[PDB]
Image: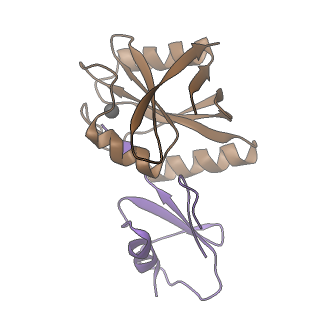
Amino acid sequence: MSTLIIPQHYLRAILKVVSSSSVEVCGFLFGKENRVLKVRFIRNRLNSPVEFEMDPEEMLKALEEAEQENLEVVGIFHSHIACPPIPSGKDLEGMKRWPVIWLIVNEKGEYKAWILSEKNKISEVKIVVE
Amino acid sequence: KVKVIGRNIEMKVRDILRAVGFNTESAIAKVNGKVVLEDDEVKDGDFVEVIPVVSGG
Ligand SMILES: [Zn+2]
């Protein structure tokens, strides 16, 4: 894709949850094409300020729920703590397994979105806050 | 009979996970639409989905 369309109230809520969390937050962006219609936070089973891994049971329940609603996974979101919202090498491997839009945010309210092409090259994607 | 979701590409379940590039800690599997554990027996005509655990930092 080339651009992420996300409603303001969802983006503001993600930033607020992140602003007061001591560990990395993670979740799904569900919708159609490039547009976010639903958000699901998922437990970070590492409970860590520097890495995240989704609870597998919560993840699967969320994907099955979205399937019932006829929604695609538009993207994944997660937070960084005390560093800018740029994909890390750790993010690179997860983006290979889930090659959708990756929204990264931090506790200072910064956010950027990224995508991994078939040539395994990352490019930034523009965000429109709806 | 092996669909890995995310990229959306199409014995016991531990071997079918290692056969497609994962282990029990990095993916969750469901057979015929039902969750299964690592040493659960796989049958010849069943349908398996491999769900990579989203991770990063
Ligand atoms: Zn990251």
Q: Report the quarter where the C terminus of chain A lies.
A: top right
Looking at the image, is B35 positioned above or below residue B15? above
Toward the front, the furthest residue is A119
Looking at the image, is A2 positioned above or below residue B26? above
Query: Is residue A69 left or right of B31 when viewed as pictured?
Result: right
**Which colour is chain B painted?**
purple
Report x, y in % for residue A67.
Answer: 70, 48
Residue A55 vs residue B9, the one in the foreground: B9
Let me know if residue A53 appears in the view. no
Report x, y in % for residue A59.
Answer: 51, 47
Residue A102 vs residue B14, the one in the foreground: A102
Residue at 39%, 35% (x, y): give it: A122
How many numbered markers are drawn?
A: 0
Report x, y in % for residue A35.
Answer: 66, 27
Query: Is residue A18 left or right of A38 when viewed as pictured?
Result: left
Looking at the image, is B31 positioned above or below residue A6? below
Residue at 49%, 45% (x, y): give it: A99
Kindly indicate the quadrant of the structure image that contains residue A8: top right
Let me know if residue A98 appears in the view. yes
Q: How is the image coloured?
A: by chain
Ligand 1: image quarter: top left
Q: Report the quarter where the N terminus of chain A lies.
A: top right
The brown chain is: A
Report x, y in % for residue A116.
Answer: 44, 40
Residue at 33%, 10% (x, y): give it: A108
Kindly indicate the quadrant of the structure image that contains residue B43: bottom right
